[PDB]
Length: 55
Length: 10
Image 1 (cartoon, rainbow over the protein chains, first blue to last red):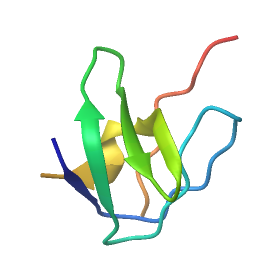
Image 2 (image 1 turned 60 degrees about the vertical axis):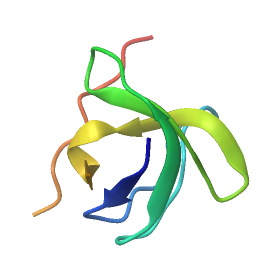
Image 3 (image 1 turned 45 degrees about the vertical axis):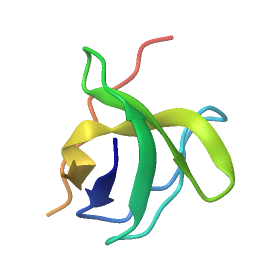
C-alpha cells in the first residue's frame, strides 16, 4: 500500500508524481511495466517508476 | 547514480 522513495523523482509528463528522496507514497497500485500508480503531493493515483522506491 | 526510469512509449 505505501512505499518510500530512494531518490528524487520529477514528473516528466502530466500523469506522473513528483517527490523527493525519503517521501512516503500512498495507496500504491502495482502493475506490470516498471511503473506503479500512487498518491503523493496532492496528486492521486499517478505514475512513478518502481525502481525509485522501496517498501 | 539514480536508476533510469523504464522509458514510456507514446
